[PDB]
Length: 251
Ligand SMILES: [Zn+2]
Ligand SMILES: [Zn+2]
Ligand SMILES: [Zn+2]
Ligand SMILES: [Zn+2]
Image (cartoon, rainbow, N blue to C red):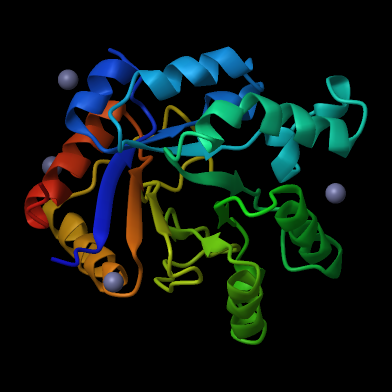
């Protein structure tokens, strides 16, 4: 029977990846955001999980305009090659859900870095890219529809986000499919403080209920749905994810 897919995952597999892959079908690994790992480490990660476990791989900080990447890489090209060279065993493995390119609050709707998003697309050939933004100008009434169209045109999977509402930068929860082949949700929790690893939010029964409605509404319109609980304390994220899984009675 033609089933559309919803996978639930965390960032804080933190015990082990091997044991994590016993309960969950999806993980987000942030490890490479801080430094590009050697190819053979990625190779072992691949070997350590079941045949159809998926990885959301967060790209190197330099790729999303955050890293001090000049310290380690001579040019943007050398940096992309190092990342894609180390990510080879995952890319060739078919266990890649998406590369997450997650931008800062300062990365907003400008001609300059729209043209940077095009550079991202080129650098990543035909690879699945989940784009995340922290700036509401991308979402402003005026520029919002071309924005979604730009994501569609480039097959970018625009990350649907639940996150703290900063008055001066209110990034909304905008459930819309830009790439019908994969939608990624990321729930950051709703605690505004420092919007930070020491900032806690445990989603309640009503919130898990609201977010589940939206997740289902999206799986109606996408082949594969990825849900990452990235709210603080892995214990909180894991509790919330286990709640959702019950609410959607998943496998
Ligand atoms: Zn366990
Ligand atoms: Zn090129
Ligand atoms: Zn609870
Ligand atoms: Zn279908």
